[PDB]
Image (cartoon, rainbow, N blue to C red):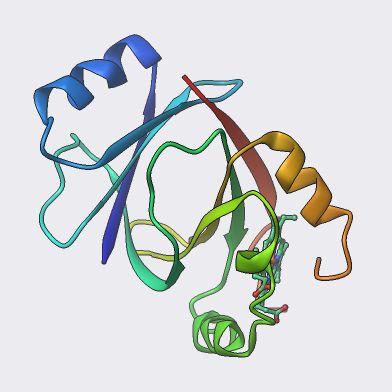
Length: 149
Ligand code: HEM
């Protein structure tokens, strides 16, 4: 129900994972830095996290091979319209082979919504992206990807 994200060197982020073994904290490696993703109903364990509310979810955050974040900046005025489109989402992605999980994350510390998808492999995501299933913006959207460590 909340998701906290933080960024930094994998070496630094690993210390947080090990400090909190009873929390489900997922570490993945990206090009610029590594990421921790912590889903919980409780409080953050990160210094100055990015905090999000979960507005749609399918699947468990476990040991995915690949993660993709669509980072979509939405104006304050556009938020109601943007969020309400998710009730109308096709609902196909969660049925594609190699899919593990999706979170649609409402940002509480910025304007940048995250559509987080977790996949068994990078190929599973590539197959989805090539398939049939798949102003209110403050700046252009961008995608970040991360791999299992
Ligand atoms: C290119 C990176 C993107 C990825 C990986 C991505 C991923 C997704 C996923 C997984 C869904 C759910 C599909 C389903 O329910 O079957 C979705 C739907 C949606 N996406 Fe994206 N998306 C991206 C870009 C964007 C951008 C730039 C926007 C800006 C508006 C956007 C707006 C939406 C909206 C409003 C929905 C709700 C369903 C719909 O109306 O199509 N997406 N997207």
